[PDB]
Length: 202
Image (cartoon, one colour):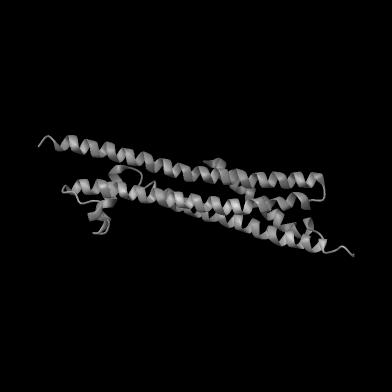
């Protein structure tokens, strides 16, 4: 989806601007431990913003490499079956879980197992992303209080909305990988099914 790179881009741009005006937004004689709190919030918000960007960028990185997998060995049962022949699982696991006589049925079984593994990896990533986001998005609120004009705080509000739109979009990419792998697992069984109808002709 190209709406992704759009959201991505708007985030990056306006995040750069906020980091630029950070000294200005939080700007600094007897009750001036309040100025400490201000410099405290400033420091905290840098950290929150940075951990958020770090999370997105780790995700953009996984997507590039994950997408290739869905163009290659996870693109069809035919290709996964091939991958699995060349790249079989260790003898322990292929015995505990895949000790069946037909050598082709072992490909199908090692295949399903591979899809399962991939699903687990993807959900863990989505979970890590979620946790990292949730623990940092709240700190972003400092921006509203710290803005001096109402006009400026509504700019910051709209900035934060970008963060959330982009994050929602990332969640959807994860969920969609999980969907593709589930559909693949079905195709693989439709494939296993035909193999068994074709096997009963000999």
